[PDB]
Each structure stands twice: as structure tokens, then as C-alpha cells.
Image (cartoon, rainbow, N blue to C red; front, side):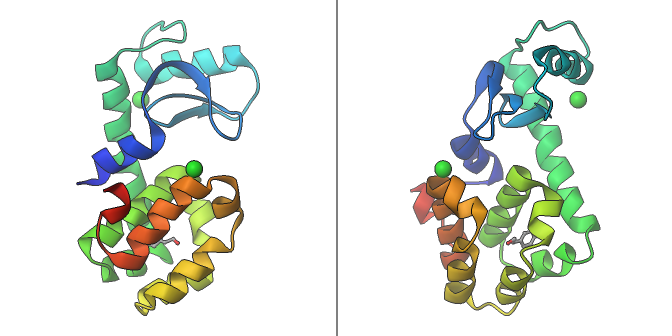
Length: 162
Ligand SMILES: OCCc1ccc(F)cc1
Ligand SMILES: [Cl-]
Ligand SMILES: [Cl-]
């Protein structure tokens, strides 16, 4: 198991513009296109990211290219964050995948407000951080996914991904 397969399991893969769980236009492997509700805005963003007139559809290779850049941007976002960096580096390799996942899903922003969780994770209080992480909108709106990430943080193994 690695970050890619993990994320691929959590986000799925779609080659046509779709609405995410929050109703926003997205494509590929969880690549958000825009928060605006104009489909045309979305198609525009799509062409811009892909470099060609897509007309709302892309190929698998194109989706995977987006995915790569997006994984990369997330890590890098983590590393550049002063509140994030230190926690991230204190964790083992599996748990670091759980961190990337959350970031990928919610932005460096969203995560940066999980202050108590961050601290608990940094002190390695697994069970405590798991309970704390559950007390969030994130868990409440996408519980099945959240559960898997949480378990990952809690255990440091890929069991939830089986
Ligand atoms: O709860 C967020 C857990 C987390 C830890 C480190 C990091 F870089 C990003 C997210
Ligand atoms: Cl791009
Ligand atoms: Cl879910």
C-alpha cells in the first residue's frame, strides 16, 4: 500500500466532470475544479489544467497526471506549513500517508485548524487523537472515509484499507 493506491481507493476515478460530496465540480481522482456552480466555469478550469479543449472529459493518463501533481502539491503544502511540518516529520511512514490524505481532501487550511489533534499526534497519543479527530464536521459528513483515515492514524498499519 502507498499514498496513491490509498487515495485512489478513497476518491475513486471518473473521467467526466462530476459533483463531489460537497456538490463541487471535480474530475479524475478527486481533482477539484472549482467551487462555483457554473459548469462552464468548471469546463474552463478543466481545459486550463489539461491544456486542451476537453469538453468535460479526460483520459485516464490525463487523470493520472493530475493525480500526480496533486499528491505532490499536497506534500509540499505540508512541508511548507510551519504548524504542519513538525508533526508530519515526527510520524512513521504509514501515518504520514494518513496526513497526506486528509490534506488532499481538505486543504492545508482545513487541517491547520485541527490543532489539538495535531498536538496529540505529535505526542503519539494515538487513541486520544483518534477520538479527537472524530469530533469534527469532517467525520460527520464523510464518516466511512474518515473512519479509515482515523484508523490509520490510530494504528499505524493499512488494516482499514485491508
Ligand atoms: O489532523 C491532521 C493531521 C496532520 C498531521 C500532519 C500534517 F502534515 C497534516 C495533517
Ligand atoms: Cl495542471
Ligand atoms: Cl465517506
